[PDB]
Amino acid sequence: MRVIRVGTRKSQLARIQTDSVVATLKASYPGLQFEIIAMSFTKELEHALEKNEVDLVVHSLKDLPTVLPPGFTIGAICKRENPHDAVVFHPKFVGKTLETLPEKSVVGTSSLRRAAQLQRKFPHLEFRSIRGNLNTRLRKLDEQQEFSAIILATAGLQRMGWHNRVGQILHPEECMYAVGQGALGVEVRAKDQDILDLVGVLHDPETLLRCIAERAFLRHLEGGCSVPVAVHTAMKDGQLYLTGGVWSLDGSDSIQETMQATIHVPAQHEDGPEDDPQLVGITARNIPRGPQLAAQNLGISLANLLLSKGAKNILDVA
Ligand SMILES: *Cc1[nH]c(Cc2[nH]cc(CCC(=O)O)c2CC(=O)O)c(CCC(=O)O)c1CC(=O)O
């Protein structure tokens, strides 16, 4: 291990996320060299990995499928940033909330998850698609009179240093977040033991266990980034709490349930067996396997409860 090559997309937010992970790595490894390789969507970065052109890539965890191709794996789940959804208001509406926008105000979001939940909670608002990156959406907000607000992840605006645009942070009772939102995943070659060990230092046990549950829930519902599925996780008092929900496209039909499981957060790293398979695409051999399997099982458990109440028919057309 000499120069650790980090591959990144050329987009602004992808670079910020990569730099943050590289800074954390450097703090654990001041004696190693890190190179950031920017290339001109996940299959192209996975190609560089497979061609040994880079050694690791940084993703928003919610953008990664629950099944990765067999030669790759998530070698690190970083300490979660703020997972909650946020509202940016049109300039004339600074200081308002969703509750106090005038009736028929148009709210911009291209997430089925966000639109379905907010339509349910706010019947008197209109939710409409809006395309573009964060800068483009904010430009269409401020330059035009079409949108009265847009919905975005709090974590994205924070990484841009634009927290001053956040006008409202949505509570779970208004809009539960996407599976993996606010956490970064580090993708690596599944068989590159040296690099898996290196990035393992980034694993945050609490976030790892929360995200295994969230992803196992999503996987067992056969969902991905695109579906109206939402979650809320918390680790308190030796319990892992997982809330999960599914919504019809307009939010009028929904199923939402909570489960918990006794799972203590590991406080120490351990030399785990190298022959255990990944869990929902994540490899964490330096973290005890017991709690990891238990988190996966909790997410499967909740998924089966939702399916028992009809979640599959909801998702099939949504
Ligand atoms: C699965 C999915 N991806 C995105 C776009 C995206 N990916 C990451 C972020 C920043 C927050 C994070 O790292 O977790 C974002 C942008 C954002 O959420 O603000 C979306 C949202 C698409 C959209 O039109 O806003 C989704 C679907 C979803 O979140 O429900």
Image (tube, helix red, strand yellow):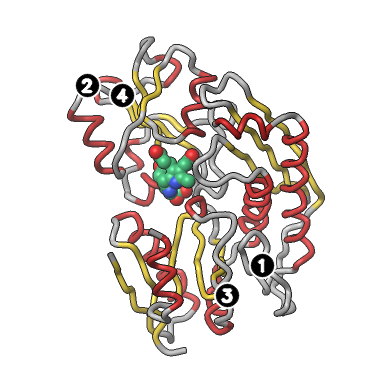
Tag 3 and tag 1, C-beta contact below 8 Å? yes
Instruction: State whether residue 25 appears in this view.
Output: yes
Taking the spot 32% from the left edge, 38% from the top edge, the residue there is 164
Kindly identify which residue carries mark 1.
278
Q: Of helix, strand and loop, which one carries label 3? A: loop
Mark 4 vs mark 3, foreground winner is 3
Question: Disc 4 and disc 2: Cα gap in Å?
Answer: 14 Å
**Between 162 and 291, which is closer to the camera in this rendering?**
291
Residue 4 is situated, as x and y percent measured from the top left of the image, at: 42, 81
**To which residue does mark 2 refer?**
145
Give me the C-alpha separation between circle 4 and circle 3: 48 Å
Q: Earlier in the sequence, mark 3 or mark 1?
A: 3
Q: Which residue is mark 4?
A: 94
Determine whether 238 is above or below 51 in the image: above
Of the residues shown, which amino acid type is indicated by label 3? Answer: Ala
Question: Looking at the image, in which quadrant does ligand 1 appear?
Answer: top left
Dots 4, 1 in contact, CB < 8 A: no
Q: CA distance from mark 3 to mark 2?
A: 49 Å
The percent coordinates of residue 153 (x first, y second) are: 43, 41
**Where does label 3 land, which residue?**
190
User: Could you tell me which residue is drawn at 59 percent across and 66 percent down?
Assistant: 203
Between discs 3 and 2, the one toward the N terminus: 2
